[PDB]
Image 1: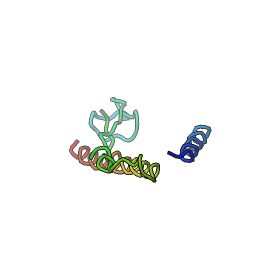
Image 2 (image 1 turned 60 degrees about the horizontal axis):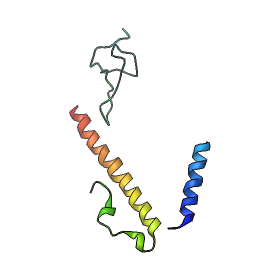
Image 3 (image 1 turned 120 degrees about the horizontal axis):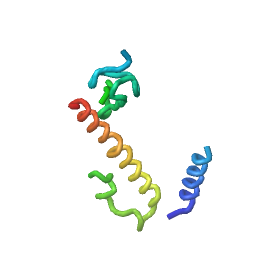
Length: 19
Length: 33
Length: 49
């Protein structure tokens, strides 16, 4: 359980939502 | 003319009397239904 | 299996590479059962239809 993958997935989701 | 028979091989949505050109799965030849 | 290879494989929660193995199982399920098997089944069913 590492937070780096969660941060990357959240950033990708936010980027695709904004676009 | 624009309207097509029931199970005639149609071309796109509408363009038929049944007005629904749905395809029954992973294949071509959309037909009115 | 119907739910990916992870059903028979041991749980990686208690071992290393947990996130990597979880991603591997998820992508295996998605790219095998959801996509390829469904495509084959749709091919057969739509051929019959």
